[PDB]
Length: 174
RNA sequence: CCUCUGGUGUACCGGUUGUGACGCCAGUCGCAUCGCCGGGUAGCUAUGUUCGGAAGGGAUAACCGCUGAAAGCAUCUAAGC
Image 1 (tube, chains in turn brown, orange):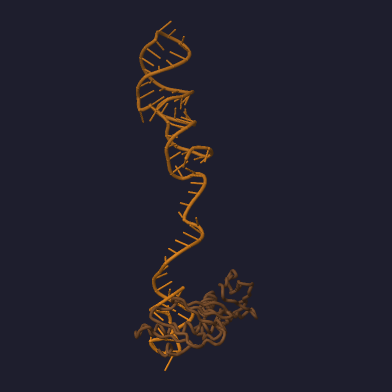
Image 2 (tube, chains in turn cyan, orange):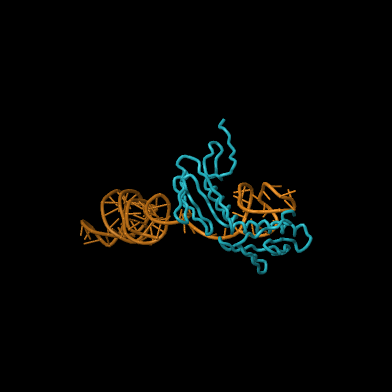
């Protein structure tokens, strides 16, 4: 695996520790832990880190590549972090933030109150846009997916919640 | 279930025909589908009354995913959620 062979960089301020199979990553953002597969081994020399299989199995190489990708995501998140961003298209579609809760008006007969999970924060510069930030890329993606699933986009006028860089399939009636 | 509305209610009350008897009048009783007819207490009962299939947890089906390599991309999947 070219991915597994590629090294990951600990930039300056994040510390990677290990105990058993539980590799922990520490930074200004916070703690992030990742259980590690039995067939993969991790070597932390100098700033860099190297993932390599404990044997010569294709399964071991696959697990090593997956572990390397996940740990690169973790170290990138604890230092810079990820933001997703979400748009709202349609008349009267609006969003607002009250602390840990997002208020959404999406054309239903009732408003929707989404409780954000611990670790992800949201901003609404304008009522049409939402910006979500977190150090956990998977958690950020899951939250964005749920908010989109509240009203996924429709193909005739593109109305509904969408990702910022999302291609929308548009057809025409009749 | 029987408070209400009703049915039934041949051991509750009354009207009335024929006949026989209680010595006779009066008053009663036997028999005639409970003789026939009109009501009707409890009980039982429906067509009457009240109530029920409300709400919530867990694992899932098709299906939709998050992150993610094998396969530098992509990918709901092989780890994991």
